Length: 488
Ligand SMILES: CCCCCCCCO[C@@H]1O[C@H](CO)[C@@H](O)[C@H](O)[C@H]1O
Ligand SMILES: CC(C)C[C@H](N)C(=O)O
Ligand code: NA
Ligand code: NA
Image (cartoon, rainbow, N blue to C red; front, side):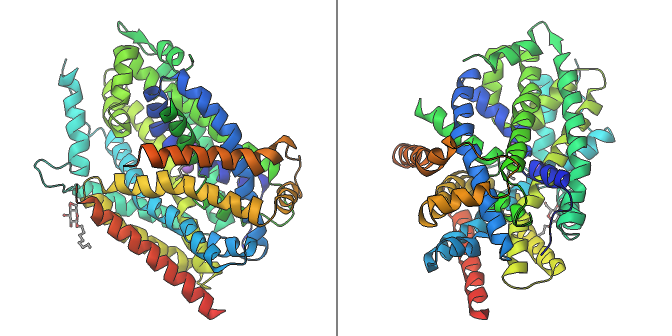
């Protein structure tokens, strides 16, 4: 079995797993949507009660299954629960990361295409708010092909489609080289490049000042202290830490049987929170508060993540010295943040085809890329198909799967056996208070917030096109698990 080469590469790959498009596009919107500092109190509590303990649990289940040559949840769930229903529930560990990748890599291709056009300077040129925002709103709308009539049909540009082929190629070139020579070798290069670009953008944004305000006013808003906020904070913690995607589990399956996971997992989770709360929150919102004030920035944040990251922020930079190049640094930061994460949610399908169907790494990567590339045409051409996948897999699915794997590992497999499996080989030991959080508090926290979510919030016909296709993806993945059974 493939293994991580160095301790540093494991941390950076796991950090690159978590540090992604959410740190810079999704977290600023959710924090500003829910009161800035008001959102942080549930966000911090969710990180301590859900994010941290589920980090250690997924590290344990991955290393446990990896020791037996099984990197994905269809087999690992069966190793922790000798039931055929554990294999069925494990399919979500293949379905969730595959569905999320189907729209994630496409949005990642947006950042690459924008970074290219912003580097060559093929960007809209506004003259001396709507008069400068419209050239950038139309720039994104022409790139992805926003519908102009009633038909919910996206018409991507030839450039956007070609950049998506390039983006898939860059993902394949990294994945096909393996864990150590591919994912780990790229993490040692991409994470320092990511941190430097983010710190520079934070510094440059902190120098923004207009009559409407300063960047410090946005920092004061996001740090000054409703069930919907608690749902938003816990959901954000899942997505930003890559929990519930089966991605941490597959990566951890290449950690050696006796290596530390307690300190290593805690460091990667901490690195992500630093990148998100310190670096990510200090760019988008402060630059918007500087140019529009706090009240308008909360209004701009409610307009969406794509609006702030692809329209508003490049339009703000277009008013500063060298802002076109600053937009390139911004979009290149997003591309490396997405690239280190998209390879992480495609590796589970790779590891499954390798471990359970005995496919060569080359074959597993190419077929996984074929499935993602083909399925992504739904996200590229059907309007709001992206939103439907992000809801079922990236929103509902991850919280459902997070509670599922905890019950399997810490209840069905045994609370004492799981706790001993987590701390085994750890440089440090998990604080004994977290044993009771894992066994009682975390599943109670998830079950309560998940019931309010289902009972109070979940209740166009084209959404069935996406539901029909991703339900078929689950059936197809179930059939592959069945074929893996028949071989044994
Ligand atoms: C199931 C998929 C069958 C149809 C595959 C079509 C592949 C996409 O085709 C391409 O899409 C781009 C987006 O507008 C266009 O700019 C290109 O002109 C077109 O060649
Ligand atoms: C789906 C995950 C890889 C997302 C990633 N953790 C992010 O923050 O963008
Ligand atoms: Na993140
Ligand atoms: Na990443």
